[PDB]
Length: 164
Length: 164
Ligand SMILES: [Cl-]
Image (cartoon, each protein chain N blue to C red):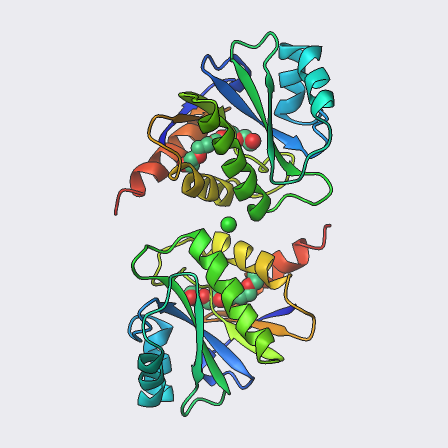
């Protein structure tokens, strides 16, 4: 899959889906999830409740309420178990599998497990990169950053990856 | 499994096994492998030749020649595929599985894939840590560093891991 890094607010992403760093109970609270629930509205949590508890490392899809995306993909990175590079790998892979299963073309992510999970961003981005490279080229992943300095860094890393 | 970080020369490790960062052809050359072959002698490569080509992510055990260890565990982190956090995870896990299968008590590792593979040490150590925690407590893993500053850093990281 293709990758781009930009500065912005993931809740204003205007594509097919955004990926939420979720707990395995799919309870929207800390981090981006809170923003997702405020701007997308109550229907997102209600749909999550219909799904019920999942497994750390799994992903689940709901509608995106009042957000300008089609879907929210809830990638469970923690909950009964603490976040780790392994849960981040599995959840990123599960999120990608849902995107491909729905024939999505544009999907936004943040650095799963690096905020609420406590993991270092550099390691998280590397495992995400490894999983994203396995998805088909019909899919474009956008990493959304709070800062241009942040986005420029990941962009620099991504160019360094071509040597070789 | 228990973990300790010390400064030293892994080829002088005086326990059950040392883990070699190998290619999947088990050809000893670049990095620690070269030191292993010089100090352990030709029998190590000869035994590797008897084994033949393995798979990136797998591990293989040989005798340690003139080294003061019982076994060399060749953890294949690269070769037909470039080194990645995923191959490092699989190889570390494969290396640990061989150690447990032989009832080993003390095993030394370096940061697999961080030298010859080009991966950043901090990410490599984190995935190794996650795999080592799954091995039984009968096993003690020693990380061997060229520098005390290096070992102290990993030791500091390991203490930070207890919060929580
Ligand atoms: Cl990983």
